[PDB]
Image (cartoon, rainbow over all chains, first blue to last red; front, side, top):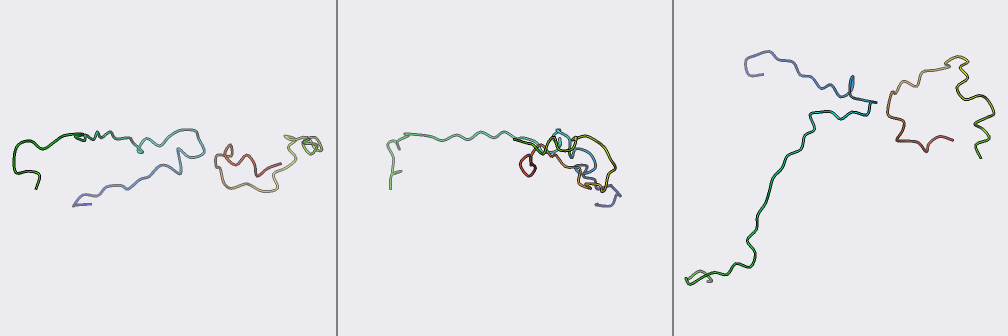
Length: 48
Length: 34
């Protein structure tokens, strides 16, 4: 990779299989959405 | 029922004829078994 020499490992077959443990690389992310509801366009030329 | 579980003693180790070669989580497929 790049110019260096690195490994390429995925452990979920030798370890973490057939046991009741979760592979710690499957993570959760949290994103919040917002939505303006009921807003009305005020005094302008904005409802064309 | 399960008369078959009682024909021959379940854990009675005679000799492994083969090796199941899988090593998976068998709690899932509980139903393909008598």
